[PDB]
Image 1: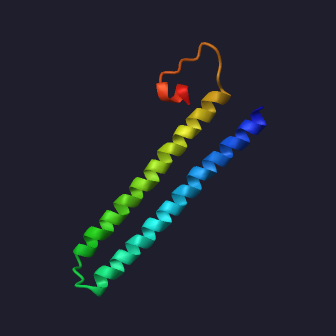
Image 2 (image 1 turned 90 degrees about the vertical axis):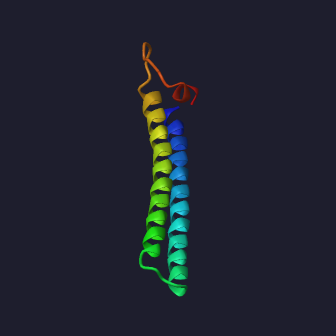
Image 3 (image 1 turned 120 degrees about the vertical axis):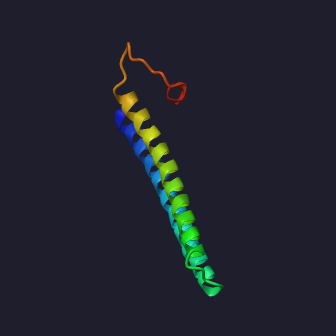
Length: 97
């Protein structure tokens, strides 16, 4: 059943990836809209610095959340493929997965 299981896993990984890409695109467009709005209004060259640092921090956050989910997936799959008796599984979360 390895072929079917790996197919399902690959599709799930791609689902995480495409969702991350959508979220990050949305947040990048929102950052550009907010910068344009600050430009239309009183444009403080430091307030736009604040909002750009905030946008980039949020994008780091989305990317890193999606990345930790992808890595969790990776460890699930490599553990199942290399599974063997006497193997110790310490993470309750990974074991229930």
